[PDB]
Image: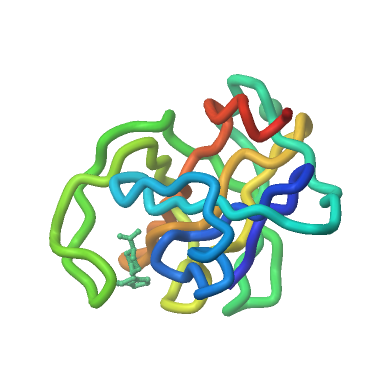
Amino acid sequence: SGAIYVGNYRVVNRHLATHNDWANLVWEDSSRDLLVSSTTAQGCDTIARCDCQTGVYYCSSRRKHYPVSFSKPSLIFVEASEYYPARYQSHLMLAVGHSEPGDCGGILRCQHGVVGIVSTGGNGLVGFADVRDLLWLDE
Ligand SMILES: NC(=O)[C@H]1CCCN(C(=O)[C@H]2CCc3snnc32)C1
Ligand SMILES: [Zn+2]
């Protein structure tokens, strides 16, 4: 589990969104595994607006932040699970790292701010849904 809290927005994995998220919906995209809802309180996270391919992510199944190198946001094939049919997820970045079911929502960050959230795992790989192109999160 986990979210990004920027401005009056809450960014979560679409597959983990709650009823309150759906009832206060701003934007959602199943192909990216992202959903954004509105919040009453202002958040403290800032979004990175950069070209980094190195950063650090939080892994809840290890209680640890790991440094990683990650690929550029791309259209990647993700294996069928109980949340999605085998398919192509867009704006996804891959790294080598531990990610097990329960780790989605952990933040990936660089020196500029939040880059994205854990969206996939398995095989010693971790996939991150990028948010750096969502410029409207800053307004
Ligand atoms: N964004 C997605 O399509 C994810 C939906 C939630 C489930 N996804 C995963 O990657 C899960 C299922 C297989 C394993 S092993 N460690 N994590 C996972 C895929
Ligand atoms: Zn950066």
